[PDB]
Every structure is written in structure tokens, then in C-alpha cells.
Amino acid sequence: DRDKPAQIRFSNISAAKAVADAIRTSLGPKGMDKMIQDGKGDVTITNDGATILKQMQVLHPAARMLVELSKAQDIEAGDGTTSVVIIAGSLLDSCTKLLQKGIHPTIISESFQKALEKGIEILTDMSRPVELSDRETLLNSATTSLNSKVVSQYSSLLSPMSVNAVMKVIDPATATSVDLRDIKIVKKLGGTIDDCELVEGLVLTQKVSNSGITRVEKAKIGLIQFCLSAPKTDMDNQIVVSDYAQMDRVLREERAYILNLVKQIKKTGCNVLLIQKSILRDALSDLALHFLNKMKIMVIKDIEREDIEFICKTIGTKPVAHIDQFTADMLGSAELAEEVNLNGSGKLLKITGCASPGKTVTIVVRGSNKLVIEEAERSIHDALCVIRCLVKKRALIAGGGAPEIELALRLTEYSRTLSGMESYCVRAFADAMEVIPSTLAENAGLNPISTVTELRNRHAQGEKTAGINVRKGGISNILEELVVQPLLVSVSALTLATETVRSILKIDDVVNTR
Amino acid sequence: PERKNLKWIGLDLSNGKPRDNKQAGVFEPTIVKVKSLKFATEAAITILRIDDLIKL
Ligand SMILES: Nc1ncnc2c1ncn2[C@@H]1O[C@H](COP(=O)(O)OP(=O)(O)O)[C@@H](O)[C@H]1O
Image (cartoon, helix red, strand yellow):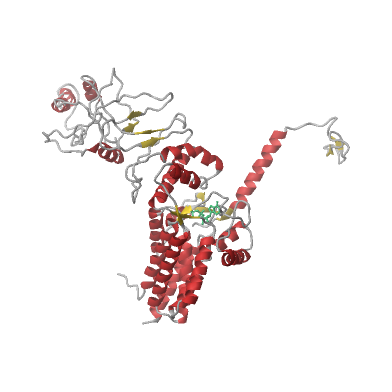
């Protein structure tokens, strides 16, 4: 009937509001910390919203939908994964009082879609475009958008890695980017972090052997995937062992059995073999390794699946399996190998990979004490992420609360100008846009209502004036502070929030189960 | 403002009478006190920065 769907909608709205209010005092650089307690008694201090959203667990359709929305927002854009929850909560709080009066959800959804389209068009018409066909303007935009993510010393430390990673000019200013398609940043322990340089081909870190000379050029990779494990017995001891007889049998089975397979395999050119991880093999027979020491020995272990996928994509080959194989589709490229250490500990080999169809290049970073390596990794990750976000479009704008107030005033004037019963619903959107500046003013340590009123008055008087400052603690113009953000991080977020609100509003009736 | 080396009397352990801790007192390293004050301030700031402890 009508009471059951109304109660279901009220319960869903209450659950969504509780989920949104469980975390709210964390937006901005001056956010509060939270100590999450584990099930065993361990406590962990954190302040990121994504970690708290992915760590906690709760069974509810609205909570699962919000988690999926946050995950999609973090995957698509990559920044600002906490404002969408507040936007959805404000929209649901507005829809609550909209439905309390007696309005059909179809008109409310149409008004929300119209308001979203108007806000998107206003954000696109207000933002200013830039250029990026050359390298000077691109480097200027990079150094202008990179000096506002972390602290000053960390920024100065990551600037060399940033300008080394931004030099990867492969796509000639296309529509989309492939920064997540052919990038494999490895990590190496030991040495100095200053010894970093872009490396093509392939980089490994496992010792080949320990014999005489191993400086050859035979494809430098063994395309083999068949089983190399020893045939396991049916039980411990099949018979009674004491004197000879049984000793000679096992001796011949250990010496004159796998050696025949090694001989029949080594009859083909390019004697390069390897193996994957030693997660299922108990112990490898060293007699086979001693017999393989002659006529050139080359073996590399500790190989994962991602390494195989990277090698099969950079070179441009396909692995083969099975034993009955009389083809010749397993060779590679021969150029140069056999590398030594770079004045320090830790074995690491590099291959530049000359004359190869795949121009994939990675960055080999280092560090010490496992303290500046992960930080630099996260820094270059955020760097290439914001670089891809900037190269995806061309529009940019500054943050602080001014665009939110501008959009709220525009929606208010549009609802005042546009006629129809839906305009009231549009007015609800006008009351669901002044949450970020109020939260920022509350977290800064000033009066939020007075600051919001002053910002609204300044926007109504001189259009584009200033916003909300954090370092100084007042109202200063943003043009002096080097801080900007792309337009996609707002447009995509607003569209996703509107879609989630429409999906959670269109779902009602009864919730049957099995 | 008359001087900075004198007029720095303190407490005494033998009895409850102020005694000048210059002609017969025991000096203490200032770096130790500075590090202790810095650690105390850091601990106070860390404790005050903690909001809630609920499993979120
Ligand atoms: N330098 C700055 N000056 C003013 N506001 C800032 C500055 N840096 C960040 N902010 C504000 O902080 C908000 C984001 O805070 P936070 O949630 O900690 O980061 P994220 O959204 O990337 O997770 C943004 O809305 C932005 O307005």
C-alpha cells in the first residue's frame, strides 16, 4: 500500500544519514583523527575517508550503494572521495522534507536532473581553458598544480621525480590517456634514492647463477611454462630399504631419469630456462643444476604473474604450454644483459631493450630504511594521477567554497525565474549546496553563518571575489595562493551524486527476500 | 633589570628556606629539559588531536 513503502523509504533515508554522519569531521587539511579499533584489540589512527569507508562493514542496501558510489568515484576521478557522501546526505535530507509535504518522486527527479544540467553548464561556462600543445605551458601547469598537495619539503623532494615522470611524452595530446595501461614502477631496497632514471626494456632483481662467465645474448628470456616438478611417490617407502638394490634404483631414478628430459629439451637452440615462484616445490634436485652448469647455465626464479604479463606485453609475445610442441615461437630480443650493482647492496639487472615494438618505460626508484620509498611512490602516484586528470580535459578552477555559493545563487535565481510546481523542488537544491564552505569555516575556527553570509554578499556584489583561507585564517583572494583543481573532479562528482540520489529515490515498494 | 647571574634563588632539601643555587647548587643539562618539554608538548598535542575511539 502506502504505509509500507513510506516506512521503507524513511528507514533507508535514516540509514543513509547515519552512514553520512558517521564520518564528517575530516574534510580539509585541518581535519580530526580517528582511532579505529580492530576485533582483536588493536587500534589504528587514521584520517582518510576512503580507508574508513573500506575498513568498516555493515549490511544494508543504502550503505552498499554508497560504498559502491565512493569506489566508483575513487576509480574514475581519484580525488575528493568524501564530499560526494555529504552531497548525497544533503540531497536526501532535502528530499525528506520534499516528500513530507506530498510531491511525486518523478517531478523531484526531473527537477534534480534539470538542476544538475544547469549546474554543469554553469561550471563549464565559468571555467577558463588553457593550452598544452607545447612543453612550457604543460610544465608550468604541472608545477602550479603540484605545489599544493603536501608540505613544502616533501614537495621539494618529489619535484625531481615529478619532472622526471612528466617528461614521458608519448600521446600527442589525445582525448584519453594510457598512464594506467603500460606502467610498472618497481621498488628496490638499498642504495641512495638520488640514483633514479627512466629505464626501458625490463628490470629484474634475481641472481642468475654463480659460475664462470654469463655474458651472452640469447633472447634473454626463456619462454617455457611446462611443469618442472619431480614425480612424487605414492607413499613414503614402497618396500624395505637396508642394503643395496633399493639404493641403486632410487639413485638411477634421481640421476638417470630427469637428465634424459634435460637432454631432450636442451637439443633445441637458445638454452635458456627458468621457473615461477617456489610456492609449491619442496626441494629442487641440485644434481640437475650441477649437470646444467656446463654448456652455458642461465636460470631466473622468483617470478610472479604480473611480471609475466608485463614481459609478454612489452616485448610482444605469447606464452606457450604443453610438452608436445615442435614449433619455434618462443624466441625474444637479443641486445645486452649481465649487469652489476650500482655501488651498494642488492642485486638488480636492467635491459634497455633496443629495437622493440613496445616503448614501455618505467621508473626504478630506491630508498633507505623503508621510510622514503613508499612516500615517494605515493607522491609520484598522485603526480601522474593529477597529470592524467589535467590532460583529460583543459578546464580548471579554484576551490574554497566560492563555486558552491555561486552555483547556489544561480540555482536560486533560476528557480525564481523558472515557472512551475517543480521550481520548489529546485529550491531544495538551492538549500543543498552551502555545506562545504560551512564545514570548512567550522573546522577552521570561525563563525560559519557569518562567513557564509559574507561570502554570499560578496558574490552578489562583486561576482568573483575571494573564498576561505586556511593558512592565514581569514578571507583572502585565491589568485595569490598557488592552488587549483580540475573541473572534472566536480562535474563527475555531481553527476555521480545525482545518479545515486535518483537510483535511491526510484527504488521503493517492498523489499522481499528468500 | 639589575643582573642575570645573581638573584636566582631556589628551593632547599635540608629545610624549607630559600637558598641561592649558584655558589653551592648543582647544575643540570639544558638540552635534557628542552627535549623533555618538547616531548611533553608533542604528547599533549597528539592526545588533544584524538577525537573519537569508536570502531568506524
Ligand atoms: N591549500 C588549501 N586552501 C584552501 N582549501 C583547501 C586547500 N587544500 C585543500 N583544501 C580544501 O580541502 C578539501 C578537501 O579536503 P580532504 O577531504 O582532506 O582532501 P580530499 O578531498 O582530497 O580527500 C577541498 O574541498 C578543498 O576546498
